[PDB]
Amino acid sequence: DPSVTHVLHQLCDILANNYAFSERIPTLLQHLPNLDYSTVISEEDIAAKLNYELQSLTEDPRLVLKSKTDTLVMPGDSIQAENIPEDEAMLQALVNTVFKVSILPGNIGYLRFDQFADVSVIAKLAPFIVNTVWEPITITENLIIDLRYNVGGSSTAVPLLLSYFLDPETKIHLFTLHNRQQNSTDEVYSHPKVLGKPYGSKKGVYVLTSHQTATAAEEFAYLMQSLSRATIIGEITSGNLMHSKVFPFGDTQLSVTVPIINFIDSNGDYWLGGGVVPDAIVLADEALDKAKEIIAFHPPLA
């Protein structure tokens, strides 16, 4: 009936112009109109049918039809540039509460922070982050970065952060973004210079994750994993990345979430999100203990 063609027509248009995997559009435009739709007469059935067909044809869980009711919640709210103090004492004080740093027994560094602010914010906090984070962990031989409570934010500072764990002179490709809505194909690299002492690329790094770890935090964890820089420990993450957009289907209670960006890591793998999968899967409460175990039993290297 008309409601099926109404959705179908909009879907094909949305896909042709937005779906990150453009190369799949020809085939999707052949199959979708070919399906047998004389069995579906309810938004729920339409969503289910098109969702089964789409996943058969794309194997991309990011592309999904859903009730408009289940369309996201709201973008995170981290420290904004327009709300950063001017006074140096207050800035150091803020940095001191944003980043929790401990030196655990056995000389293992512990770094916790629960949001990723925009790079414009990090720029103004960088001088203070030197004192709270980078200098104090210099003495340690291994570092545990706790992101179990980190609901992310903007990814704009991820490359910069990552650069503290890589070679000062290397220019490392991190990932490449392909934004369909335009022709991004932007290659993202590490920075050749950071402020404060890089932790370096040699010492052991362990990233703790939970099901609450989100957006920028997932990207950070994923990238540390994809670069073989750290061991990820904990739960599979939330699967909330900022790679899609939602498109409502006019005249219906349905919408479609479409990935508009593809994220290709330094090994050429396309990350479909849905959650970073830890190297050592344990419940979130056990992750710190696990990391310590790993550290304690690491081969003394012959």
Image (spheres, rainbow, N blue to C red):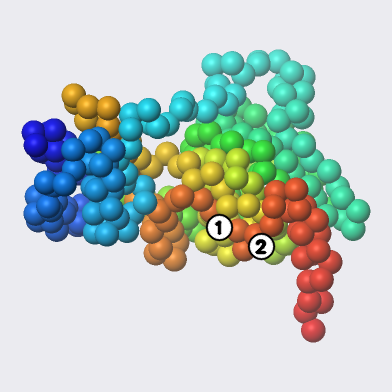
Residue wearing tag 1: 277
**Picture quadrant where residue 166 is located:** bottom right
Foreground pick, 241 / 192: 241
Tell me the kind of residue under disc 2. Answer: Ala
Residue wearing tag 2: 280
Q: Is residue 281 shown left or right of residue 263? A: right
Q: Is 126 above or below relative to 237?
A: above
Q: Secondary structure at mark 2?
A: strand
Task: Return the residue found at the far bottom.
Answer: 302
The picture places residue 65, in percent across and down from the top left corner, at: 29, 40
Q: Is residue 8 shown left or right of residue 122? A: left
Q: Secondary structure at mark 1?
A: loop
Tell me the kind of residue under disc 1. Answer: Val
On the question of residue 208 being in view, the answer is no
Task: Return the residue found at the far right.
Answer: 105
**Marks 2 and 1, Cα distance to the nearest angstrom?**
9 Å
On the question of residue 107 being in view, the answer is yes
Residue drawn at x 51%, y 40% is: 215
Foreground pick, 154 / 29: 29
The picture places residue 226, in percent across and down from the top left corner, at: 52, 61
